[PDB]
Amino acid sequence: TYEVQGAFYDSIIDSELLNAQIGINLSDKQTFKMKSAPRITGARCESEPVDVGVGAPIVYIDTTGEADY
Amino acid sequence: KDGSTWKQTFLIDAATGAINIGLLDAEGKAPISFDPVKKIVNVDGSVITKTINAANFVMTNLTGQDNPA
């Protein structure tokens, strides 16, 4: 999680003064939660036995992420 | 007659009413095969008929990666 606060600094503001953040008059802070990358909980593969022919392979894999896609 | 050897084209066994039709594959897979013992008619390829009457149209994934439908 991070907190965001910033503002515009004009030509008057100096690098040292900007670091001091004295005259900047920054914006109020705001807190947001940073999402989590996907991970795979387990890897597996199972298929149905068949009397005639061959069982089609399939992969079952369980994730734990929160990505949109 | 292929060179100095002879390749089977079709066979009709006496003990079993099995009739293999077609030149044999390098691995020995006959194109069309029959078996009254198992009461099955085995044809690799396609079958064209005006109509078909049956009691169970059980689609099968005959090949490793086929899509029955």
Image: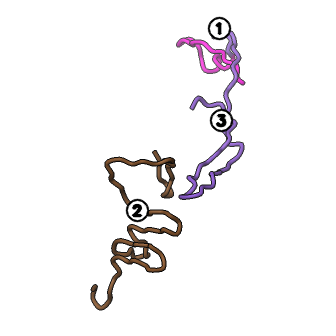
Quarter of the image with the N terminus of chain A is top right
* Distance between mark 2 and mark 3 Cα atoms: 49 Å
Please give the chain letter of the residue carrying mark 2.
Answer: B
Quarter of the image with the C terminus of chain A is top right
Q: Nearer the viewer, mark 2 or mark 3?
A: 2
Q: Which chain is purple?
A: A
Q: Kindly indicate whether the residues beneath marks 2 and 3 are on one polypeptide chain.
A: no
Disc 1 marks a residue whose amino acid type is Asn
At 42% from the left and 68% from the top, the residue drawn is: B33
Picture quarter containing residue B24?
Answer: bottom left
Which mark is on residue A25?
1
| Nearer-the-camera pick, B37 or A40 | B37
Q: Nearer the viewer, mark 1 or mark 2?
A: 2
User: Where does residue A52 sit, x and y in percent of width and height?
Assistant: 55, 58
Q: Is disc 1 placed on a helix, strand or loop?
A: loop
Picture quarter containing residue A62?
Answer: top right
User: Where does residue B34 sit, x and y in percent of width and height?
Assistant: 44, 68
Please give the chain letter of the residue carrying mark 3.
Answer: A
Which mark is on residue B44?
2
Residue behind mark 3: A37
